[PDB]
RNA sequence: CGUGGAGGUCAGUGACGAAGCCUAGACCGUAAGGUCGGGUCGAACGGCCUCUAGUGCAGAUCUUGGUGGUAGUAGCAAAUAUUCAAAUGAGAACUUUGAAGACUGAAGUGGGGAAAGGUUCCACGUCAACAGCAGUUGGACGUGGGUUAGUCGAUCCUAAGA
């Protein structure tokens, strides 16, 4: 069930890295069947792949 | 019988440190949580939770502030098991400090 | 399970589908004529034109019934025209055609479905020249020889099967067919299967087999019960070991059971399109992109092919759909079968002349004559 | 093929191998020498005891740089170990063997294992990679473990012989002179 | 005296089992040895009288190949850290997915070229050897596909040089 390809393939879409994406262990019968970029960009507007909270750097102290 | 009784035991995962590296505290916890469950409930094969692991790894390896409040819920196990069906399930909750608390019997209400 | 296991409405749906199947098949038979004859009319008949016509006809008629009804109707099996040797499933793509030639033996097989209920029919006949040039030359003359022998044998088989209903075993049908076929000296094509139709399901595991010792063991004996539907198929050969010489499939069905994630976009799109279809069996003729898409799907087994098989010099077929049920009259309940196919299936017995006939006199044959009569 | 020394009737015996697996051959030898005396079911319940590490077979042969154990006052030698991974291979030889005697018409309740054989599995093209000149072979040795069950004691019958002894003429007259006094 | 080999002879022996190996089986001889039996094995064998000399064997740091004691041994310490859950499986501390806790802090294990290499990249499938523990993943193995150019290069020209 190696899905390192699908994650790396997401970096060749726009510019999203391989640690900002968010999948789901629930729908494991959908990701395994769709082992390509054919059903990735459509799994965003429906509510499947997000980013949410990300640790960043502020300059408010500056 | 299966009993199935939800209880809240007193156990802190921050002070129990003696001659153990601070990067290998987790293997000690394996022989601690399963031991704490065997001492009270009485089981070996204990399945935890994704949110359960976050309770230990709060803000660092020793992110545990003071005295926490864990809630072990003994349930039944099927799906053709090999060990005891009466496993343990710790339910982490929000708690600042445990003062004057020893145990809480949680029913169905 | 299925509540409302049987419904009056269900019966109606089959009957209506059957009526259309019957009409369409009659229409095609009328159309079938020699190429030269068709030329006089300023028309052309080939394996493709009839197929196209018949499929269109089924769509149109279905459209009339339950049209726009919260469901689906249409073509259960695409129209297929075999020829003398060719056993079945010949529905050519536009890209080799087959021109009808006087004296050819033709088998037309088609199916219609209303809301998933399927009515399938088949028929065999010989081709004759235009009436106008020939005036009742063909009616005066009968068909004789092997053609007559096979056709009669197939028909009789069909008649035997109709008789042979709840409380009977599939095996009895198989045995009878062998006896009847042998009477001419014909043989039923090995390992063919009849199905026990359900809604949205042409295939049915329960089946009656035409079978070598080998398939006898894998075949499953079964007893027919009330409220069961069958599509009895009878294929007979003057020669009965069919083979896939080399012909392009053309007929395919989607297999619900298997699922695969197909790599190509074209294939994915094809898969989606096919799912939309309504009947399991569609023809490719429904062109370009399809060829590519079919390849991947078939490989995966998403689609199941209906191959065309052949017997050179030497096949006749009759297929009808029957509904079996329990009727109660005179305080007695007995199974009775109703034949949906109708006129389409029928053939004129007078046309065929055969040297041989079933002969009840010998110990082997006796009883068949009575069964037929 | 054949087998080892036929101490009992081969017609009423079952066996099984376990080669090309993993665990070596002398490692399962020590537990094969201590099993010579058990009664079938004494080894089946022993399998679970190993995973929990409760009983260790006295590794009496292998002593050099072999650490002791607390489990030593069971038999004698305090140098013993636990055949952990061997358990999954021991059961391979067993269980199936009980089914082999089932077709023959026997029962696996009296046929205890006493004659167990173990050899040395073959080698392949294996070469080491050390300090150039210190390269000979990487080849080792898996296993060829096979155990043969044996029925219990059934009608021993020592059958004392007549014991022929060269008697003399002055001996037959001596014994006859004693039976006329005491007897 | 024994072994290998050639010629001649007892017009020998030979699936009623040759020759070779083992034999806590026996007889004869001071020493070199041979014959018989059993087991294994199933194809051409042995003695005497001659000839031929690359025939016999504890060591030349002898040559090549294979196998022990040591030994179920030493070693398995450059580089902060593992643990929990889910899917698959007979089998998981380590591959995949998600979350938490961290290392390296564009002078890094980044992202683009030349040289070497020419199917080690991508997809699918598999776990008998190798991959010095494990490892369903992989740079192991088998079955396929991709190679598209008026323009960034090269080819053309020149110094050194041949």
Image (spheres, coloured by chain):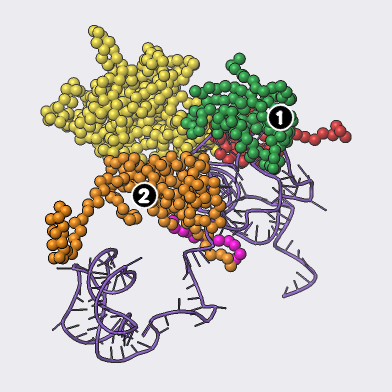
Chain colours: A red, B green, C yellow, D orange, E purple
Looking at the image, the residue that sits furthest to the left is C361
Query: In the rendered view, does B82 fall on the left or right side of C339?
Result: right
Q: Position of residue C222 (x, y in %)?
A: 29, 26
Q: Is residue B100 visible?
A: yes
Q: Residues within 10 Å of mark 1 (few under 14, many from 20)?
A: few
Say which quadrant the N terminus of chain C sits in.
top left
Up/down of E58 relative to C283, above or below: below
Residue B38 falls inside the magenta stretch: no
Stretch in magenta:
D121-132
Say which quadrant the C terminus of chain C sits in.
top left
Q: Position of residue C259 (x, y in %)?
A: 49, 33
Up/down of B19 relative to E26, above or below: above
Question: Circle 2 sits on which residue?
Answer: D114
The span from disc 2 to disc 1 (Cα, nearest Å) is: 68 Å
Q: Give the residue at x 49% y 28%.
A: B78
Q: Nearer the viewer, residue B70 or E3?
A: B70
Q: Name the secondary structure under disc 2.
A: strand
Q: Nearer the viewer, residue E77 or C104?
A: E77
Q: Chain of mark 1?
A: A
Looking at the image, the residue that sits furthest to the front is D181
Query: In the rendered view, does C265 fall on the left or right side of B15?
Result: left
Q: Which label is found at residue A52?
A: 1
Q: Give the residue at x 26% y 20%.
A: C167
Of helix, strand and loop, which mostly describes the magenta segment? loop
Residue D124 falls inside the magenta stretch: yes
Residue D110: name its quadrant: top left
């Amino acid at each position: 069930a190696n899905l390192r390809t699908q994650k790396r393939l997401a970096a060749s879409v726009v510019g999203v890295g391989k640690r900002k994406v968010w999948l789901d262990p629930n729908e494991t019968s959908e990701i395994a069947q769709a082992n390509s970029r054919n059903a990735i960009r459509k799994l965003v507007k429906n509510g499947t792949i997000v980013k949410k909270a990300v640790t960043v750097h502020s300059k408010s102290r500056t | 019988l299966k009993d199935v009784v939800t209880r809240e035991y007193t156990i802190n995962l921050h002070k129990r440190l003696h001659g153990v590296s601070f990067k290998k505290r987790a293997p000690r916890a394996v022989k601690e949580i399963k031991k704490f469950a065997k001492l009270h409930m009485g089981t070996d094969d204990v399945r935890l939770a994704p949110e359960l692991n976050q309770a230990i790894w709060k803000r660092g390896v020793k992110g545990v502030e003071y005295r926490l409040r864990l809630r072990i819920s003994r349930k039944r196990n099927e799906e053709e098991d090999a060990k005891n069906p009466l496993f343990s399930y710790v339910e982490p909750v929000l708690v600042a400090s445990a003062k004057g608390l020893q145990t809480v019997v949680v029913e169905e209400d | 399970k299925d509540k409302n296991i049987l419904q009056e409405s269900v019966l109606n749906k089959y009957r209506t589908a059957g009526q259309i199947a019957q009409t369409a098949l009659k229409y095609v038979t009328s159309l079938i004529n020699d190429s030269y004859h068709s030329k006089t009319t300023q028309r052309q008949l080939t394996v493709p034109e009839l197929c196209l016509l018949t499929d269109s006809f089924i769509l149109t008629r279905l459209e009339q019934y339950y049209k726009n009804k919260v469901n689906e109707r249409g073509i259960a099996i695409p129209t297929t025209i075999d020829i003398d040797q060719i056993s079945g499933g010949w529905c050519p793509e536009i890209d080799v055609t087959g021109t009808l030639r006087p004296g050819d033996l033709v088998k037309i097989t088609l199916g219609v479905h209303i809301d998933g209920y399927t009515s399938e029919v088949s028929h065999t006949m010989v081709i004759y020249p235009v009436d106008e040039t020939k005036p009742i030359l063909q009616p005066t003359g009968p068909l004789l020889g092997g053609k007559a022998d096979a056709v009669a044998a197939a028909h009789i088989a069909m008649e035997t099967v109709v008789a042979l209903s709840s409380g009977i075993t599939g095996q009895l049908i198989r045995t009878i067919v062998d006896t009847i076929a042998r009477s001419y000296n014909c043989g039923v094509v090995p390992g063919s299967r009849v199905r026990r139709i359900r809604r949205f399901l042409a295939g049915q595991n329960e089946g009656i087999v035409a079978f070598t010792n080998v398939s006898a063991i894998p075949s499953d004996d079964f007893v027919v019960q009330s409220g069961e539907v069958y599509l009895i198929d009878l294929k007979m050969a003057s020669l009965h070991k069919a083979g896939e010489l080399i012909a392009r499939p053309g007929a395919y069905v989607r297999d619900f059971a298997q699922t695969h994630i197909l790599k190509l976009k074209t294939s994915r799109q094809l898969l989606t399109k096919i799912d939309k279809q309504g009947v399991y069996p569609f023809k490719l003729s429904h062109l370009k992109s399809f060829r590519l898409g079919m390849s991947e799907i078939s490989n995966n087994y998403l689609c199941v092919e209906s191959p065309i098989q052949i017997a050179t010099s030497t096949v006749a077929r009759e297929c009808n759909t029957i509904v079996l049920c329990d009727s109660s009259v005179s305080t007695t309940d007995r199974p009775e079968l109703l034949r949906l196919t109708g006129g389409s299936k029928t053939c004129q017995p007078s046309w065929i002349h055969s040297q041989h006939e079933l002969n009840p006199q010998d110990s082997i044959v006796q009883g068949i004559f009575q069964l037929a009569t | 093929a054949r087998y080892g020394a036929t101490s009992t009737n081969p017609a009423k015996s079952a066996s099984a191998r376990g080669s090309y697996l993993r665990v070596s051959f002398k490692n399962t030898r020590e537990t094969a020498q201590a099993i010579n005396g058990w009664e079938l079911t004494k080894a089946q319940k022993y399998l679970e005891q190993v995973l929990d590490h409760q009983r260790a077979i006295p590794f009496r042969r292998f002593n050099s740089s072999i650490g002791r154990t607390a489990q030593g006052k069971e038999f004698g030698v305090t140098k013993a170990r636990w055949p952990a991974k061997s358990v999954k291979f021991v059961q391979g030889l067993l269980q199936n063997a009980a089914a082999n005697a089932e077709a023959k018409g026997l029962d696996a309740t009296k046929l205890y294992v006493s004659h167990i054989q173990v050899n040395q599995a073959p080698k392949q093209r294996r070469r080491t990679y050390r300090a150039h000149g210190r390269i000979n072979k990487y080849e080792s040795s898996p296993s060829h473990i096979e155990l043969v069950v044996t029925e219990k004691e059934e009608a021993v019958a020592k059958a004392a012989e007549k014991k022929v002894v060269r008697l003399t003429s002055r001996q037959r007259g001596r014994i006859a002179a004693q039976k006329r006094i005491a007897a």
